[PDB]
Length: 19
Image (cartoon, rainbow, N blue to C red; front, side, top):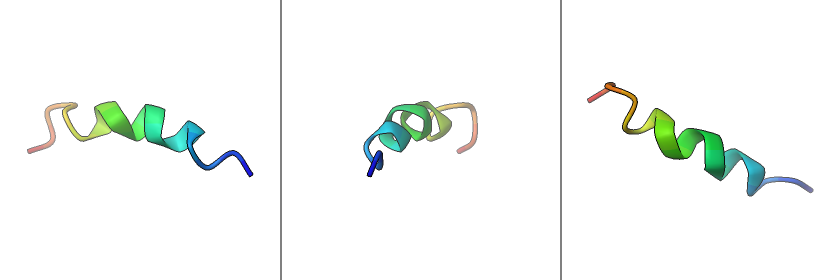
């Protein structure tokens, strides 16, 4: 159940110039 693996990618999606 690799659910933590998603916390690595999204971790940057929050600061990927989204605001």
